[PDB]
Image 1 (cartoon, rainbow over the protein chains, first blue to last red):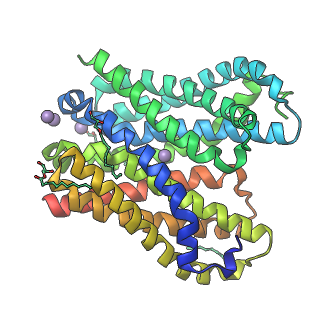
Image 2 (image 1 turned 60 degrees about the vertical axis):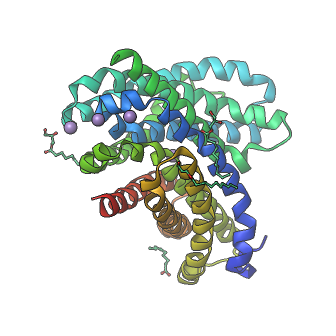
Length: 178
Length: 177
Ligand SMILES: [Mn+2]
Ligand SMILES: [Mn+2]
Ligand SMILES: [Mn+2]
Ligand SMILES: [Mn+2]
């Protein structure tokens, strides 16, 4: 589609379907949170860190994904190299997790919620770790399924990290505060 | 190149950008803290935070993708940003009303009637503003000589999380308190 020649109505028609699919899939997060209503009610400040946790996961995943998409498209990597990449990214994700978690724990202490220092600290490490792997592996999976990663990698990694991020954080919270 | 670098080298190359983003993203926790009153009154408010901020990010990044492409192929010039701004005003409102209709349905299903106008109004505003942010950012970056490929997407997502939260919680406080 040519942007400069497309009217508002035309742009809406070309954009809406992808957004509808994403928000329908995104509604899952609201159901997840409802299933943890007990823990959310128990500790008020638990909800304060959801956007930065899910957002950091998304940032990490889309960073590693972009690196992989480029590496494959430039033939620096091949589809057969996914295992060696996986093993290497386990280390990178762990190192990134520890670094970012160290900072966020500082914020939690600043905000004055010492009860949440362990749950937030552990959760972000796990979230960065898994989001980094999802980001590194998705371009391989997409390519093998016939669709190039460049077109749809961003919203997929963002949605998956949101779902998996909520599940990790709230589960860690339920085990440590109950 | 990727096949070259080891784990520490990759960590070295990635950490600075992620640190800047999280230091920026930390503001969201401070924003939510400032609305603790209404959050405590209606706990269900927290249920729709990720889907609201996430839809804003999706909208913004979809918009940014189109603009980056048009600038690369010279379908648009740098000075066209005002005309793009005015047109995207309409597109965002149309996408906002469409997506809002769906999410209100989810709220109606979940059984939180108090949040029907809160979530409905917020999503329209969130989509509307996130769309403009996504459309304008490539103009700003190219003006500063920055390549969007590894910068545009995390920036839109973080800006939308902050602005989206400010909209949602302000509407919540207004309608519930
Ligand atoms: Mn309850
Ligand atoms: Mn409570
Ligand atoms: Mn507090
Ligand atoms: Mn996000």
